[PDB]
Image 1 (spheres, rainbow, N blue to C red):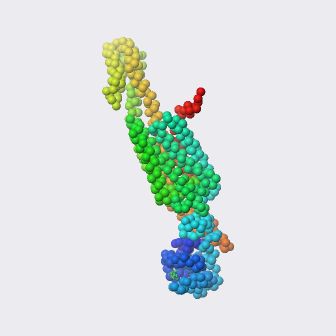
Image 2 (cartoon, rainbow, N blue to C red):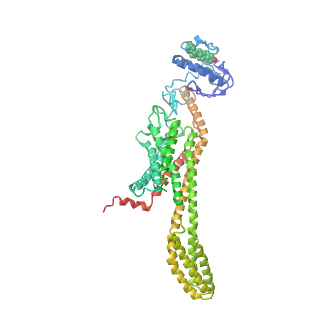
Image 3 (cartoon, rainbow, N blue to C red):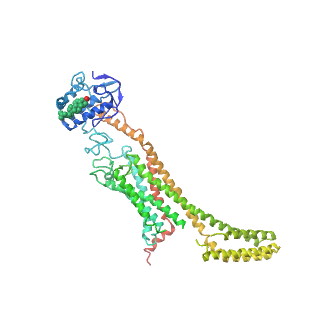
Length: 581
Ligand SMILES: CC(C)CCC[C@@H](C)[C@H]1CC[C@H]2[C@@H]3CC=C4C[C@@H](O)CC[C@]4(C)[C@H]3CC[C@]12C
């Protein structure tokens, strides 16, 4: 009979000599030189050396597959046919010459019954139409998926259909367009006034927007007439993997270099910005030539490293080439680590900056408090009847004015000498009015308070109104740094979240995809043999919404840094260049 009784075990390898197996179970009973599937892989590795004889290899492939890795299903294994065995004797007679034929490979009808339907005869080892979606026939050995011969992994992402590709593409279109023209607006602002806007750290924003401009250029390069397929796909319609590979158009690695280098420089310029802010608050242009070197070297070294390990992969969905798609331990290495360190450092100099800021924010506010006390107490004194209120409020004025005088790089400067003298006059007159108030003389002290008013205006109002507008500037800086802080931290948190999700479930997504590939590989043979075919699908796939969020995060960063130039002071600068008369 064409069937033998044995226990079916799962295929440890779903490929038989470069050809996908349409079944999932096998048995090592027919392979009388093997007891386990590991042994089977060893013996087939021994048979592998016969591939240098295409004439024999072509004819011995189906026999070897039908014997060593047969289809087991429901406790039954199908034995290879007599004809199949006879198709091997004539061309592979060489095997009989050197070492002879194994007894289980001899065409004895007990091993190879006559007229038995075999599942392998349907399989074509040289793929004319064997290549089944998501695989495309490529004769280039650098594109072949795993060990499979003739078939390569298709270019377009086999996890998302066209209907999703168009969606994500128009999404990226919109966002990257907004970013490219916003960044272009910032650039144009700091460029038309290149003579007046070239200052630190105001030019650091210009550099950030420059980087995020180049990056968005790289992101938009995929929208030309047939450029996308030129960047993402190889010459044989298989997705570019492990780039840069030899003898392939550099249309991919260029885009990768653009996107990645521009991104990394664009996010190290953040650290430079925070440092520049801290040093600006702590007080200069002595280290202004050293920031460049870091911000251009580190992304360069990183990019060169990625090109050195050749881990540039092409994505049809995003429409670009980026690091660590296939191997997710590279994206976490070259994206999450630098961005993370950037977050740490920039955060450090941010909080340092707002500490250097908070230390003065309290001082100025205290001086203002003293002034407040002076004003309200003068309000009470000028308009009062009881001579106790005058004494009290004059004492309070004395305390407040004394406390204000005890404030501060040179305490011996002529300004500090003068400022304290005014409070000497004020405190003195306050004490005179105090002497008047103690003796019960109400209206005399009240009349001696107007002296305090005119003296307040003359000697104190100067420095006060000088340090009155600063509390607005300091608060504006504080709140805009609050903005930048709680925004950048948000973006980093979100992108770290997305990247971590993909990093988490990529271990399962590959499993699902592989199972799917095997399933459709079964469908291929199952169709052209009038056999019942099973519906195949992907068990689980990456969420498009997550990628949407990540893109929204990075492009959101690209937009939020372009918004910084959007001020009322900018709009008028444009007019100076061409207003004429
Ligand atoms: C004819 C001359 C050039 C020798 C060619 C050697 C190669 C092509 C062939 C000839 C005979 C073949 C062997 C025949 C018998 C066996 C025993 C089996 O359990 C393992 C495979 C093994 C070991 C084969 C390996 C491949 C083999 C060694």
